[PDB]
Amino acid sequence: DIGQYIASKISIIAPNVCFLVGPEIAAQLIAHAGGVLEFSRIPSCNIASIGKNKHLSHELHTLESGVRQEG
RNA sequence: AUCCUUAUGCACGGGAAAUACGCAUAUCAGUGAGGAUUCGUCCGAGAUUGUGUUUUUGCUGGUUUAAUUAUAA
Image 1 (tube, protein in one colour):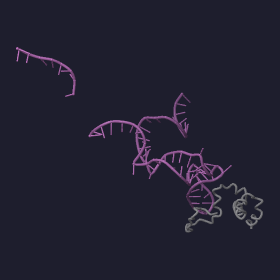
Image 2 (cartoon, helix red, strand yellow):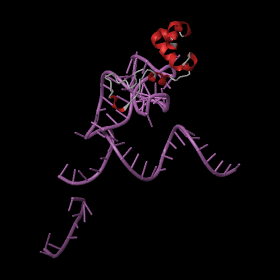
Image 3 (tube, helix red, strand yellow):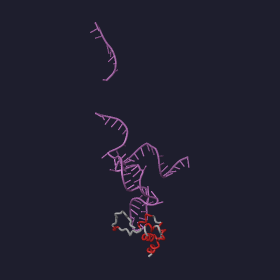
Image 4 (spheres, rainbow, N blue to C red):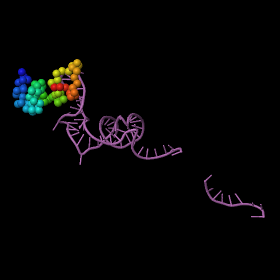
């Protein structure tokens, strides 16, 4: 419910990130770090791991892209 | 005044390599290159593209016989 509410009003709270990535994602991001401040405190190398479901030994994942982390 | 730490320059002495060292009126790159993870995160400067030489650069060493002149007539 919170996440869906953020996606509606997010263009007000974070107009830039919803412009680059889009609101459906930025809502998920901000939704994770639980604010704009706490998400801007995050280094950029830690941002790509957010949507990553989980890592487990039998998953068997090497992409053709070379992406280790899909967020 | 002695003693010590870091960085840089010159240098005696001792090693290792030359699939190794460079170059660019060229593209990006701490305003994040390239990776790593135990999935929470963690490390933090090169990567592309073209090219020169690379069983080799410079320098060296070895091997393939003077003049003068003497007899008793």
